[PDB]
């Protein structure tokens, strides 16, 4: 389950991922490592921005 | 300081975080809003990602019962507080005992450790460290992340950014455990310590704005007067529109010698003069002229993102995200500070020996000293009467902060603003005092009227 | 499997809402019906409140 870092820009309850795991809840402004499926959907909804962490 | 006892707490906190990472648990990170907390949050966020773990970072103004209750309802496995929590140890014991808690802070704690199990306080103060000069909140985060994985030493510059934002080097140099972080960054080549002018704006501000906005130290007759700063730099042979980093090394020495002489002539305190040239932390990772190239300029950008409810955007900058840096600059005061005090100079309370202008939240508590100097250098107040600007402390809703500024000619009436502010500080309940011509005070907000009568009576008695 | 299908069209769902809708998915309502109900409420999150209102409008008891 590929995961990336995102800044969630709205309040958000715990939501399910494809792995049936729970993710959240999120306070508006939180930065979390979440499955890309959820993050990309929030990005497309203009509700989150990707953040790159160079390791 | 008992450094070895402190390192034992550092390993405890680091081992707990890594244990939950290896258990597959999301590391819940809570960090403070200012530059110290934003860098501390990014240090721990990168440390968790480097171990292959998962985090969810919240940048908050303060730890409160309402915040702890929200965190408790999330039902997490481990909560990690950075740059806060030292004053909330019993609140955390009560509402988060069901989970692992790690507090990484440098503020004086109410208890030297937790009584509950799987709760570790990582704080150097109980081991003999100076809270305001031996290590900052980001420094504690750095120690914990370095114990988790020595590759996290590549965040040494980010930690110093928070240390400079926390004014750990207020006297021009670093002390205590900060020096261990600086040596780490030097070994990795990610930071360099210059001996230069310590004023803000060596990367992005013109030289006249660098001088006019000087606060640590202030420059007499120049702080708060952009016109005199432009005039002064021209007479000394400098382009006032040039940036400090663009000067040759010989041109910088010329500026330093000229500024130091100007401060000796106009009776600047020896403390202010000794702090003009000192440690300035630079990072080769960024181009010169970039805001991130210098620690103080970097810490200034982070504090800006924190005041616009965009703290994690500042965290993303510390993690190397280039788009977040571009977003922050497009998203982002002294000109409005002068416009406010001029267009609202009907709100003052002139007594028999001073002015008192309470601005509320309209002026930051850090710009109060500049605002008082601006009232003198803008045809607003009689230069023979000292000026005191007051503003609500952004860190305490029940407190207010003020600075007392006057001119040299007015000093020749018996005035001394340090002894005047030290007297009222010990008659209202709070800090206060300073030097002869410049001093500050912090007292309860509900006794502003008592301050004006006492400070005028104290000044008139001099 | 409505978690993946809603995610395919950029829709999130809470675990409690999945509890109330999973058994009814594809039997009593279509993915398009649930998506249209959510979009007309101006949301892309399917929570327990939206789920109960959705089953109510559909007559699913």
Image: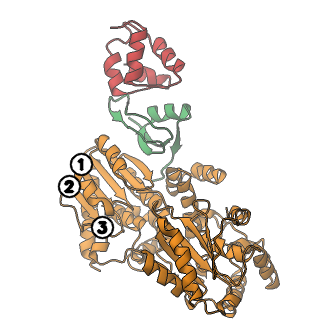
Chain colours: A green, B orange, C red
Q: Secondary structure at mark 2?
A: loop
Q: Which residue is mark 1?
A: B99
Residue drawn 41% across and 69% down?
B136
Q: Are marks 2 and 1 in contact (CB under 8 Å)?
A: yes
> B177 and A26: which one is in front?
A26
Res B417 seen here? no
Q: Is residue B257 left or right of residue B462?
A: right
1 or 3: tag closer to the N-terminus: 1
Which mark identifies residue B109?
Answer: 3
Nearer to us of marks 2 and 3 is 3
> B378 and C43: which one is in front?
B378
* Alpha carbon separation for disc pair 1 and 3: 20 Å
Q: Which residue is mark 2?
A: B118
2 or 3: tag closer to the N-terminus: 3
Q: Secondary structure at mark 3?
A: loop
Query: Callout 1: few (<14), some (14-19), or many (20+) C-alpha neighbours within 10 Å?
Result: some
Residue B116: name its quadrant: bottom left
- The subunit carrying tag 2 is B
């Amino acid at each position: 389950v590929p995961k990336e870092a995102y800044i969630i820009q709205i309040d958000l309850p715990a939501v399910l991922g494809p792995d049936m795991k729970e993710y959240g809840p999120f306070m508006a402004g939180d930065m979390a490592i979440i499955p890309t499926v959820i993050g990309r959907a929030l990005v497309e909804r203009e509700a989150a921005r990707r953040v790159r962490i160079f390791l | 300081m008992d450094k070895e006892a402190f390192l034992e707490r550092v390993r405890e906190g680091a081992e707990l975080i890594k244990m939950h990472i290896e258990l597959g648990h999301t590391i819940r990170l809570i960090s403070h809003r200012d530059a110290d907390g934003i860098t501390a949050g990014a240090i721990l966020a990168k440390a968790v990602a480097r171990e292959g773990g998962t985090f969810q970072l919240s940048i908050v103004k303060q730890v409160s019962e309402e915040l702890i209750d929200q965190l408790a309802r999330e039902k997490r496995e481990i909560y990690v507080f950075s740059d806060l929590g030292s004053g909330s140890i019993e609140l955390i014991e009560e509402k988060l005992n069901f989970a692992t808690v790690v507090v990484a802070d440098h503020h004086p704690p109410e208890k030297d450790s937790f009584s509950t199990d799987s709760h570790v306080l990582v704080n150097p103060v109980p081991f003999g460290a100076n809270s305001v000069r031996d290590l900052s909140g980001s420094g504690v985060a750095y120690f914990v992340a370095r114990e988790m994985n020595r590759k996290n030493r590549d965040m040494a510059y980010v930690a110093i950014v928070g240390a400079v934002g926390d004014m750990q080097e207020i006297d021009g140099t670093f002390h205590g455990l900060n020096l261990e972080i600086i040596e780490d960054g030097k070994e990795l080549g990610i930071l360099e310590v210059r001996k230069e002018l310590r004023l803000f704006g060596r990367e992005s501000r013109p030289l006249y704005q660098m001088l006019a906005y000087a606060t640590n130290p202030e420059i007499p007759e120049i702080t708060g007067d952009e016109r005199k700063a432009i005039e002064w730099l021209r007479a000394k042979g400098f382009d006032p529109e040039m940036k400090y980093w663009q000067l040759r090394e010989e041109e910088k020495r010329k500026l330093h010698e000229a500024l130091l002489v100007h401060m000796i002539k106009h009776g600047a305190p020896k403390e202010a003069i000794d702090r003009l040239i000192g440690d300035v932390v630079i990072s080769p990772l960024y181009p010169e002229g970039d805001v991130r190239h210098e620690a103080r300029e970097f810490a200034t950008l982070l504090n800006a993102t924190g005041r616009l409810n965009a703290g994690t955007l500042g965290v993303a900058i510390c993690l190397g995200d280039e788009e977040a840096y571009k977003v922050a600059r497009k998203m982002l005061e002294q000109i409005e500070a002068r416009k406010f005090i001029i267009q609202n100079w009907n709100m003052v309370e002139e007594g028999e020996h001073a002015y008192v202008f309470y601005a509320g939240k309209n002026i930051r508590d850090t710009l109060v000293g500049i605002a008082a100097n601006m009232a003198i250098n803008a045809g607003l107040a009689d230069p023979e009467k000292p000026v005191v600007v007051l503003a609500d402390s952004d860190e305490d809703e029940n407190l207010v902060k003020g600075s007392a500024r006057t001119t040299e000619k007015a000093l020749e009436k018996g005035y001394h603003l340090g002894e005047a502010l030290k007297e009222v500080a010990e008659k209202l309940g709070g800090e206060g005092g300073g030097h002869a011509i410049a001093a500050g005070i912090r007292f309860p907000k509900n006794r502003i009227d008592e301050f004006i009568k006492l400070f005028n009576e104290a000044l008139g008695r001099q | 499997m409505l978690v993946e299908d809603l995610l395919k069209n950029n829709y999130l769902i809470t675990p409690s809402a999945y509890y109330l809708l999973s058994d009814h998915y594809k039997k009593a309502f279509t993915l398009a019906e649930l998506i249209k109900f959510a979009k007309n409420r101006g949301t892309f999150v399917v929570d327990s409140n939206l789920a109960r209102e959705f089953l109510a409008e559909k007559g699913i008891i």
